[PDB]
Length: 186
Ligand SMILES: [Fe+2]
Image (cartoon, rainbow, N blue to C red; front, side):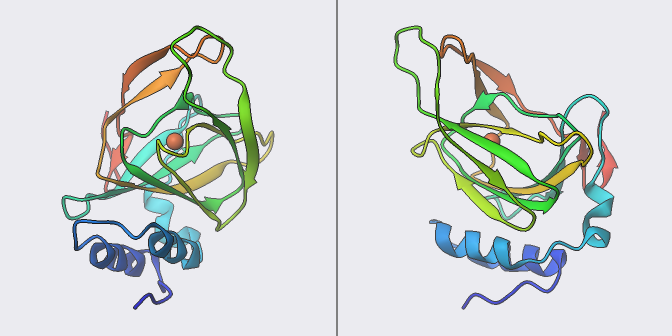
């Protein structure tokens, strides 16, 4: 039974239930994430920005099966084109807007990676990606408004690949946490 999360803490409790088993009901998790109405006071602790790039701020370590984190995107900050390491990845906007550009997996041949589509993710929307859907780049294209997003990955992963848009060639990247549970982790 899926109920509206009343608060971020409540959402987290609900996620622990949704991931209590071995499989993941993506549409249910997405619906639950979308249903949480972003309340800045509840996540201010995790919203630690860096002037130069987006930050990843661990919120909950999950139950072995998932991780929940907050990403903070300064004006003009964006990601590489990347995959998600065989994990489910949910992205819910808590503040601002993000542009998501989708790309197909490249062929072995070196070639320009051309976008298959793009969309604007708006406050409170929850998007979902996995490797079967494709690769993506996520960017805050705003000149004036920072963005904050809530990301859920299952299983947890701490590496992915970044892709060279000009060639499709990939390089492994180890992902780091800017903070964990509200504590800066240099
Ligand atoms: Fe991503």
